[PDB]
Image (cartoon, coloured by chain):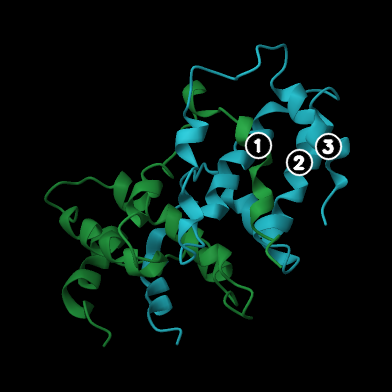
Chain colours: A green, B cyan
């Protein structure tokens, strides 16, 4: 099923705004997302393109205008990321922005071993 | 396997700078990253944890005292989440954080739906 089809995507024209350029000022994310999942050593990118999409709806608050549905598409990103378990939740709001003193703690700096190690 | 740290991890001691021994009436770092990986179904944020990191070393540039470090430390990290292909390096420069108009051309927000199936 290609599901939530017709009413939410429907308003994508709500973010495209007042008529119709093909987003024609620059061949951009068309250029970005070109060949991407290419070959089974993927993971990375898909998750992050999805990070700015996430700061996309968070930034666009226009309360009546689309707002409820940015929330409705951003909600299903869940299933785009992981959403197997509840804790998927926690981390992203964490995964927000602005480092502050109180969050430029870097001590646990070394941390990174744990991944590619695991034979 | 993965010793190379002798002169490089030794630098973390140079970040900390002058002293006390425990970075702060924190637990924070500790309370932060404790049980994350607990369930290997969540690949995703591991990439982003290292992103603030990219948001740290690309923030300090300490002139031959700490620079080289951050240089050296900054590098090893792609090799953690993804040393898989040559490409992704590019894919980060974009990932800078500040999307300055003419750069948040959200037209395309609509295609990533595809991760939907994958198999």
Residue to which mark 1 is pinned: A109
Locate residue A91 relative to residue A60 in the image: left or right. right
The extreme left residue here reads A64
- Residue A79 higher or lower than B33, as above or below: below
Q: Specify whether disc 2 shares its chain with disc 3.
A: yes
In the image, residue A115 above or below residue A1: above
In this rendered view, identify the residue nearer to me: A60 or B37.
Answer: B37
Q: In which quarter of the image is the C terminus of chain B?
A: bottom left
Q: Where is residue A61 in the image (x, y as percent from the top left)?
A: 23, 45
Q: Residue A89 carries which label?
A: none
What chain does badge 3 belong to?
B
The residue carrying mark 3 is: B8
Task: Determine which quarter of the picture holds residue B6.
Answer: top right
Q: Which of marks 2 and 3 is in front?
A: 3
Q: Nearer the viewer, mark 2 or mark 1?
A: 1
Chain ID, mark 2: B
- N-term mark: 2 or 3: 3
* Element type where label 2 sits in the image: helix
Residue in view at x 35 percent, y 47 percent = A90
Mark sitting on residue B73: 2
Q: In which quarter of the image is residue A97?
A: top left
Cβ atoms under marks 2 and 1 closer than 8 Å:
yes
Position of residue A14 measured from the top left corner of the image (x, y, whole percent): 23, 61
Residue at coordinates 60% horizontally, 52% vertically from top-left?
Answer: B94
Q: How far, Cα to Cα, is label 1 from label 3?
A: 12 Å
């Amino acid at each position: 099923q290609g599901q939530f089809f017709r009413e939410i995507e429907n308003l994508k024209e709500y973010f495209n705004a007042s008529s119709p350029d093909v987003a024609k000022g620059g061949p951009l994310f068309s250029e970005i997302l070109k060949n991407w999942k290419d070959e089974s050593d993927k993971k990375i990118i898909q998750s992050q393109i999805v990070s700015f999409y996430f700061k996309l709806f968070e930034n666009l608050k226009d309360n009546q205008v689309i707002q409820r549905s940015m929330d409705i598409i951003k909600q299903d990103m869940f299933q785009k990321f992981l959403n197997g378990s509840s804790e998927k939740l926690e981390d992203f709001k964490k995964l927000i922005q602005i480092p502050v003193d109180d969050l430029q703690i870097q001590r646990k700096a070394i941390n990174e071993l744990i991944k590619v190690m695991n034979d």
